[PDB]
Image (cartoon, rainbow over all chains, first blue to last red; front, side):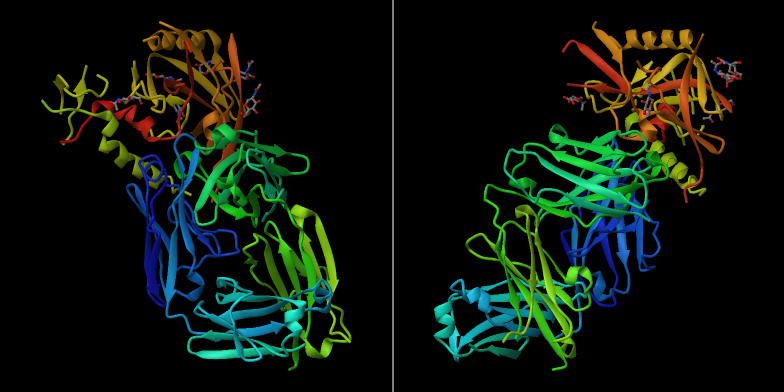
Length: 210
Length: 221
Length: 207
Ligand SMILES: *[C@@H]1O[C@H](CO)[C@@H](O)[C@H](O)[C@H]1NC(C)=O
Ligand SMILES: *[C@@H]1O[C@H](CO)[C@@H](O)[C@H](O)[C@H]1NC(C)=O
Ligand SMILES: *[C@@H]1O[C@H](CO)[C@@H](O)[C@H](O)[C@H]1NC(C)=O
Ligand SMILES: *[C@@H]1O[C@H](CO)[C@@H](O)[C@H](O)[C@H]1NC(C)=O
Ligand SMILES: *[C@@H]1O[C@H](CO)[C@@H](O)[C@H](O)[C@H]1NC(C)=O
Ligand SMILES: *[C@@H]1O[C@H](CO)[C@@H](O)[C@H](O)[C@H]1NC(C)=O
């Protein structure tokens, strides 16, 4: 394949340059280098085609160049919407087509945002199956690191907890879920479960009750 | 200018044949474009599988898949197809369908300007399991939801009121339990004043197990 | 004594670059004998035709950076040309006899003691599966099936340059070997334009 650094970090406002190193049979044989942005839960978006051309509308901040068997993509005035994976690719002799390995771009300086937390109690319908799942949904926070703590009537809750790993939403913030799996009997065995989400020092708690 | 939608089995057993289809709307596959299949496995990067050219049906393949890939085009129905033979778990990936545009290929190649959304395909011996669907209910604004519990494999579709409700819909990524089963939750944030007036229904779709469920979500007695 | 090398000719890649550049419309040691060897005994001191399968209007023998290597392209040069007429009405007449004699002459030069067969391009790219070429604004895509399996007629597709009648001498060819059996199968090649242009710059160097 074609080689790119796996990851680069820059900051808001700066410029970044991502190199794609190819061979004499792809990048050196054609002006056929294309670049692709890829956000999570989105399809790859075309950025640059034929070394340096743009579709409307990908901004003026994006530009591609070529030098021998090596192509480059440069991004100026980094905005938060640019935190993405970036791929270079090219037509290759013998009628094949080849992608680079990908570069994961990190953008520092993104403004912090506090998590919205929403806690749901078990449904009567689930309880009738002798089970009880408490659902703690956590959304719109940045950076994407959170700590979830469950309490039952005040006491720490160790078992029955499964928390997802944070993922990016379409608005460039993060989201995660925590699920406390219980039996019908445990749910009634207490009289107030709570979810404690802690994100950059400060802490939000929601509380449900049988 | 053109829309593409992939579809096919969500689950395939090892050594069996993976089969997918792209339905192209807004243009005709008999035109002067390449129709490509591309994929991405969890953790890995993009990978071109191959292409068929609309004008005459000629194909190109990734040299390391050549021995077990075919691609076809259906000029009525306006569809392109991928058949990948003798799969393994390394064939688990999101599969994309993309249009290839070009000026003069011999100088400038071609490039992928329109893509579908991709369809996940999972290669495994695990059986399928459809989910159970449960309602989530308890400011000036209220949060209602559906809990989609214990299914395999991913993904599940959740819409609200047949797709007629969009603003405020948030479907969270699935959690994986040590049982190997997935669960997720979809939340929609409605005007608090609209309750008792508007009706809210989640539409849950789990294609690999042919599970279609509508759940009414009310604030109960 | 110092060596030529048409397969690592930096001249080729410089002229490649600038023809590509132009297509956004939208000292030197000469050698006489050759084949791009090391030593060149006799020492002195360009049509940017974009085409595939065939070479048109060039210097008027087979050359390969590595023949054992089926992936390597074979540049073919003819001792006698073959006139090919192409019309905007959409086809190409070609002398059947004149063309058939050519293939078999190339076929004895390939035996360097076994069966030689020519077959159509394996599939995939339209500008390669066909004998394609530009010709004063228009761009022809002609099915060369009859060519690579008293006139022969070739159907042609024609596009003017909207992206962003002419006669010709056939100088030479570009060929690909199926290298996987007591038979050597040859199919029409092309794609890397640099081959078109080292087909001509084989007998030059820079020092
Ligand atoms: C030519 O190709 C053959 C097979 O690809 C290889 O064994 C041989 O070393 C090559 N000769 C060179 C590179 O000089
Ligand atoms: C093609 O036209 C040219 C005139 O330039 C000449 O070779 C001859 O008249 C024609 N040859 C054919 C039709 O084979
Ligand atoms: C040959 O070429 C002439 C003009 O180039 C054209 O009128 C004719 O239709 C072609 N084919 C035959 C079979 O004569
Ligand atoms: C000529 O080439 C076209 C395009 O490659 C192909 O569709 C057609 O079948 C070919 N003609 C014949 C008679 O096979
Ligand atoms: C073929 O080349 C010769 C010179 O080599 C030229 O005189 C002749 O006109 C050419 N024929 C055609 C049809 O272009
Ligand atoms: C080859 O030469 C002939 C005669 O000058 C000309 O008509 C034709 O356009 C040339 N071929 C190309 C591909 O330019």
